[PDB]
Amino acid sequence: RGELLVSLCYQSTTNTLTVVVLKARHLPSDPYVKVNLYHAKKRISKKKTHVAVFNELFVFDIPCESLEEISVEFLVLDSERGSRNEVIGRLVLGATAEGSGGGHWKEICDFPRRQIAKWHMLCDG
Ligand SMILES: [Cl-]
Ligand SMILES: [Cl-]
Ligand SMILES: [Cl-]
Ligand SMILES: [Cl-]
Ligand SMILES: [Cl-]
Ligand SMILES: [Cl-]
Ligand SMILES: [Cl-]
Ligand code: NA
Ligand code: NA
């Protein structure tokens, strides 16, 4: 399913979360990335890159005092005129994400104000 390089930084003093979509590799196409921010299970924000180096920094406002019920969803999509863009791959980082996102997310919580970059495997989405 391919790989996605993301950097995250929990700027806790301002309650912001910065997210950089850097790049994808080994994609199976006209890729862009959509980024959804969830509070508990409600989407509270969304971003997307242009349409595979992406190099795009986003700043999210966190409405609560911690990242405990926050999750970030990355979708790598193939842009195609005249039909629904197909999800090439998917990545969720959060407090109960599979393993990848999970530990990257934990490290973000453990080292606030640090930028931590990591390669993650994409899943089906
Ligand atoms: Cl490689
Ligand atoms: Cl989209
Ligand atoms: Cl979406
Ligand atoms: Cl949408
Ligand atoms: Cl650039
Ligand atoms: Cl932004
Ligand atoms: Cl890595
Ligand atoms: Na935001
Ligand atoms: Na389309």
Image: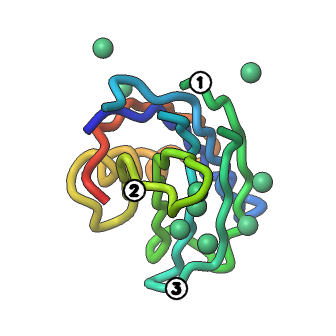
Residue at the farthest front position: 82
Marks 2 and 1, how far apart at CA: 20 Å
Q: Residue at x 60, y 45 (%)?
A: 9
Q: Residue at x 31, y 43 (%)?
A: 122
Query: Please, what secondary structure does the residue beneath circle 2 have?
Result: strand
Of discs 2 and 1, which sits in the foreground? 1
Q: Which residue is mark 3?
A: 42
Disc 2 marks a residue whose amino acid type is Leu
**Left or right, residue 109 beside residue 21:** left
Look at the numbered disc 3 and say if its residue's Cβ is closer than 8 Å to ligand 4: no
What is the number of the mark on residue 108?
none
Marks 3 and 2, how far apart at CA: 15 Å
Q: Which residue is mark 2?
A: 93
Say which of 125 and 7 sits in front: 125
Q: Categorize mark 3 by other alpha carbons within 10 Å: few (<14), some (14-19), many (20+).
A: few
What is the number of the mark on residue 53?
1
Look at the numbered disc 1 and say if its residue's Cβ is closer than 8 Å to ligand 5: yes
Disc 1 marks a residue whose amino acid type is Val
Question: Residue 5, how many percent across, how many down?
Answer: 46, 31
Q: Which image quadrant is residue 94 in?
A: bottom left
